[PDB]
Length: 155
Image (tube, rainbow, N blue to C red; front, side):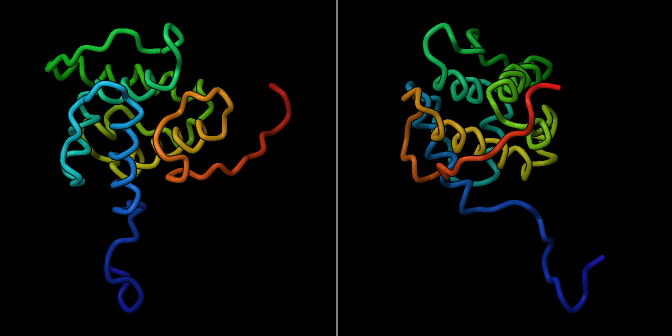
């Protein structure tokens, strides 16, 4: 049901200004060339859909051995790929990001919530740029170096 007078198009939480930056960063973060796909929003989904790439990202950050996803193989298998995505998320949260923002394995694999994952990533970068490890790559401007505040100790 269209709003009517105020609201021509859907108020989706997707942006084409951040997508362009993502592909630019992701491709950078990862040393090797995963295969910088098209800048379109139709491919991006397929890029991470497989899962491989995603791994290259989280793996690019953490140092040798520290990387959460050591095994990285592009298994055409539909069952494999999906699971391949979780391998990243599992560490995505443990890294610092909040599960309340993290997308779902299917949300991306099937591209149901391309708006969610499209953001979940941006957070991965903004957080890294807030660290002092000196691993993060690509222009630090892309993501905000702003600092957030956490609650009370565990409990």
